[PDB]
Length: 319
Ligand SMILES: [Ca+2]
Ligand SMILES: [Ca+2]
Ligand SMILES: [Ca+2]
Ligand SMILES: [Ca+2]
Ligand SMILES: [Ca+2]
Figure (spheres, rainbow, N blue to C red):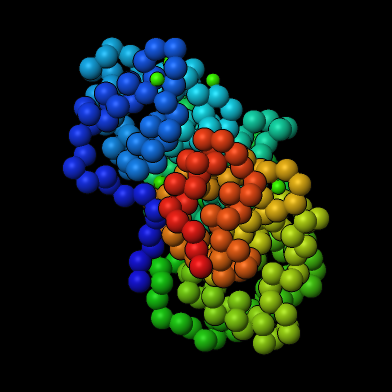
């Protein structure tokens, strides 16, 4: 009945003892990576910030600086991601994605399509405080087409409240989305962007259902997942996030590991950002939709302490 992550507050938390444990794991020429990853993956993000404070008070050193030099590679990147304050994670990920012509549209689409209006409001406020600019201005400056416009509408976080189902509106919206897809999402973009971006989640769930009966196929089938452009990818992420945010992010994890190579940036990002929100539900959708557990997939694609920390973040095997 509730969303649910895999990381919770550690019972009997003593930030000073945890700071000594992390310092003992790093003081000297050696490194106890096992002790570091066991402690940090079992402490909540808020507790990690308290350890960071006690670490500086007791020893006069910066914990994040110590971890960066003591650790290397993907394990270091995972630990650094876990130490970033939860209030700042998405805003930092978006600013990093908005890098000129090398803009990472996947990160923009992933965060902006799957975050709630309340989360997007906090992101916009934190983004301004950190980088001196507005997220909208940075988005408009680095994106184009109606992909930019759909990102702007979603960022406004003005989605209608979950209210009573209006059958006349569901029929009119499903008809319009069918005619927009017939034109390959290249005509009257403001029209379907307004439907995708400002209609309530429960309303759009019904619109997607009325779309199935009217057209004979689900609305996702009008967009090729691999070859489609940015707007169509964003539409696909919004539609899937409307159905189930954990299902969309589980599919995102799945394709980050399917095939050759591993999208470790996406693996780390989704694992960490959702660790205290809905990573458990993501695991449930992962097992249900891809016939294998998130745990077993991480075990087969990663290595070293990076794999150890990822599996502990995952929590447990499924099935
Ligand atoms: Ca050392
Ligand atoms: Ca040591
Ligand atoms: Ca390093
Ligand atoms: Ca937020
Ligand atoms: Ca891959």
